[PDB]
Image 1 (cartoon, rainbow, N blue to C red):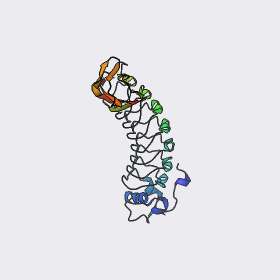
Image 2: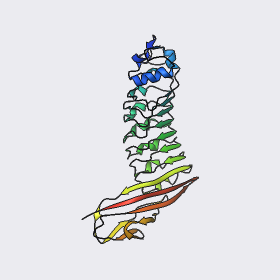
Image 3: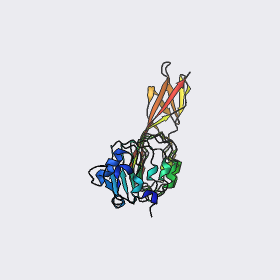
Image 4: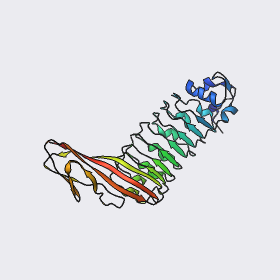
Length: 291
């Protein structure tokens, strides 16, 4: 059963258990109490299945350890950083923590019933701790600082994955995730779709607004940039529109460059069909120039 350290044996005022008054108030509401000064029993705490507390200025969930049966936690738009108090919530199934600053993800390591996790807009770069959640079904990681998604190769139960608005170029870790149905990858740095070829169960796929930044090359009148953009079959994607009246002579994008232009670009576009999913693979390759 629960740890004695995580159980109350006497009626205890809410405010003494939940150190952050915002979270204490949340519990008071959940339990329909008049005030955080009111006592609660463990039986009352055990009855909490779901906490909805978005946009509540919560800085700490200290005390939540006393809620062994909580399965759903909606905590979007708060001021959380540390999620250690969640560690032993073995029944947690849904955890929404968008718009916080949660980075220490190994506190989730023993949440083996967690099926849906949302951590959008947390400033996260390191998702390695997610390796301990192989049962995950939905994962939302939009608007973060992620580059390395290596660990996602272990999340073979995901059917929904959002990685939009990160800094990802290497999507090879996704290649074996054939259970995927909804995959959101817009606003990354993706130029090569080979990784997606086998995702036969996709229904929704977003691949637009990629930004691909090349290392600077020398400014010269006859400028050449090799096209590196690849479709799911490995073939080059012909540029859509090339800046500065440039042209494409496969495989090279070419410009007759003016002295006063110091960066060129091209937009690429490829319609993608993978199983039922139809997607716009779209982006821009930017080529800064140096003297």
